[PDB]
Length: 350
Ligand SMILES: C[C@]1(c2nc3cccc(C(N)=O)c3[nH]2)CCCN1
Image (cartoon, rainbow, N blue to C red; front, side, top):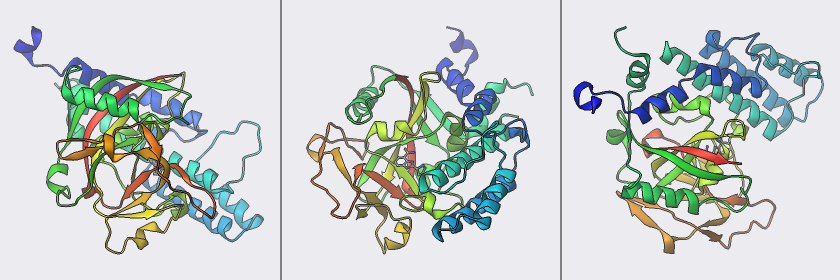
């Protein structure tokens, strides 16, 4: 009954904060991604250096697009590796020549960007954990495991776990309601087709996401890193987003975010187009159409947002040209179409 006297941060919030603010975990995560933390300590990384990294990736993009492989491309990849040091040990540093390889470097810089944010943020009479939490300017309130909200979100979590993501299952360890300063008032409440949708991210990135909100891509990032342009990406299948947690048997605790997304009218597309944003022409979002999705007969709503409970079934969508997405994804291009609402602490069972 100590809390009636002294009013502490709930233990579950303390443990969350300890988890996402762990700078050692960030160092290990970047070393796994082949970033050379010894040559370029994360503490000294600046926004300008990351920006310069993106500009080198753009030079690489120019080269890939022109089919170049000689001097221009070598010069570009060397420049990139000079600006964003990597550790390939004794192995030839690899060329960056495909969309997937470009995207991986982009995700490395996205992580570096959120790390730069976190290290600044975690720098009195106040306990370090109270200080970190305050500095997020984002309320996080644990929810009761016997609440209605917990039940619906566990159902959404399990029932939208996709059949082709069978290398793990997920256990919901804890649940927090998220109220980020400003989002309620900015949100596009007027738009129809408001859905509660998934976003996953690496564990290094949550200090940045909670303190700044979900953001569109850096303006200097190569556009070809982004399947449907520089928007904020969401899934209706929990495991499509959870894959982007990059959890593993070694590090099997990750987080998953649910947000209210004001989709309005969707421009529906069957295959990648990085210039998708320019195709909106008055519509409000992009939907990449998948072969399998939850169907409306099973939907429920939670506080005005449609919750697309599974199981997934065939959508009857095939592309007669080539590749079709396995599952849907949704893209909005203004943060005011996003209101963060829940954060799940997830145990991944490999
Ligand atoms: C490749 C990329 C990405 N695509 C997604 C599609 C559905 C969900 C997510 C998510 N993170 O939950 C996605 N993330 C592009 C933007 C950042 N990473």
